Amino acid sequence: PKLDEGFYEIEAIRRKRVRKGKVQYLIKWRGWPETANTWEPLENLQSIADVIDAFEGS
Amino acid sequence: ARKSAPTT
């Protein structure tokens, strides 16, 4: 569960699964090859600030 | 977004 130290941009959400009781999304990362795709839980993809701003703007 | 480092 160790994170890459960097910050990255989601290009596409490709697939969904459940691992150990947690939903994960297969992410294609912008600027990176398809071989770099990773499975991530929601918390890695979405901050609380993201959720609130998205809500307040809708 | 944050990313998980690959398995080694």
Image (cartoon, rainbow, N blue to C red):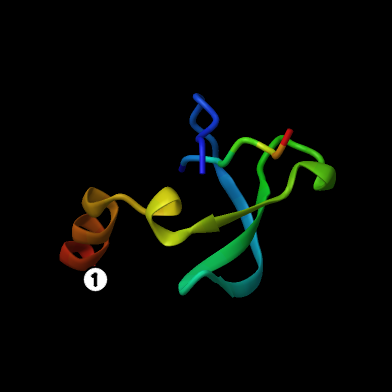
A30 shown above or below A26: above
Image location (x, y in percent) of residue A21: 46, 74
Image location (x, y in percent) of residue A48: 23, 53
Depth order, front residue of A21/A52:
A21
Depth order, front residue of A33/A5:
A5
A13 shown above or below A3: below
Side of A45 relative to A15 (left or right): left
Image location (x, y in percent) of residue A4: 55, 30
Report which residue position mark 1 lands on.
A58
Side of A40 relative to A53 (left or right): right
Label 1 sits on a secondary structure element that is loop
A46 shown above or below A19: above
Chain letter of the residue beneath label 1 in the structure image: A
Residue A31's image quarter?
top right
Side of A47 relative to B1 (left or right): left
Side of A58 relative to A39 (left or right): left
Q: Residue at x 55, y 40 (%)?
A: B3
Image location (x, y in percent) of residue A10: 57, 49
